[PDB]
Image (cartoon, rainbow over all chains, first blue to last red; front, side):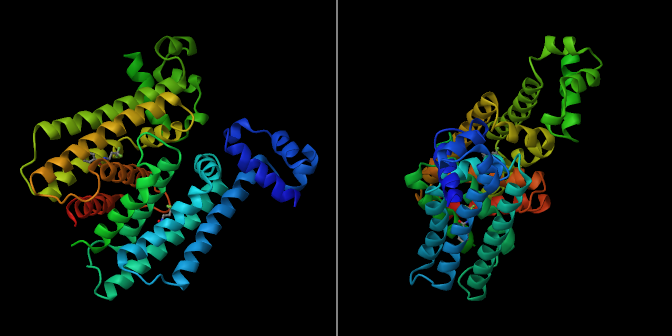
Length: 191
Length: 191
Ligand SMILES: O=C(NCCC(F)(F)F)c1ccccc1
Ligand SMILES: O=C(NCCC(F)(F)F)c1ccccc1
């Protein structure tokens, strides 16, 4: 409960400044508690980011499980769009956590490992689906499915996050979904 | 001259530990000079990284100008491979600088702007070539050329650098060139 308060406060404060510029004291008063009461719920401001990013990533993950268990009744282009869109919408709704999470991969081993565990899972799911499409005679046996899936997933990570942070250069947010779908569909079905 | 010594020393020390863990004193003795003599050539260890990354990136840039002025006499797949290979070979030969440079984008505005200036130039060159291919009737008018070029360049940045750092996940270094060429050629020529 106070736990949700510290989390919401961190997400809000990260909408306006980096983690380096937010104090434990800043998070404490935000949730309406003392510095020492803060330390009962979290070991550090860094563990607060790790928890937010845990929640964002698991939300993406569950949303993609829900898609996998309940296929959308559509063509191959839309099957892939619906999947990429889990990442667009989920992270797109949590840009501050997304951006702060990505910078913490450099400094925090737990953040790096969390990102790494989920990226390995999403790449493995992507490759299994390409393999199914190949077994069905729907896609040609070009590159190793897992090598292809790895590059395409790395493209979506870099390209979504550049867009969300308004980096230069970046695809504009309103064009990025279509851009990625074109590259997935041409690279998975092209000869 | 002592300048080249500080640069070589920094590159060597970055083959073994991050910049955070290298002192000005560490760079100074490396080049066989005093701390204060160091400060005559460079304002900081951070300006030393900025200079290395300047050199790496300009080397990539000149190598791609040389390709553009002197076309390779080959099919479209090899034209693109020869281009992606400038980035593979150049950065691939300077992984420590590459990796330390990429982490410094987060903390250093000069590093971020340098990376941003060159990425904008390589994306602009990529789009002009796709446009030429389209004007020639060699590629179909699918996505906006600059949106396509931006995503494909962002894919090569993330995917090359994950490979070079042996990240998990990543395409293995010996498979990454072929992986990227397949995605460029299918996405640029596919309908
Ligand atoms: O879009 C994807 N991956 C991007 C994951 C991200 F953004 F890098 F975290 C994806 C799409 C369909 C099925 C599986 C994965
Ligand atoms: O491979 C490329 N871009 C990647 C640039 C990098 F790696 F991201 F720095 C490229 C290929 C052909 C022509 C122009 C650019």
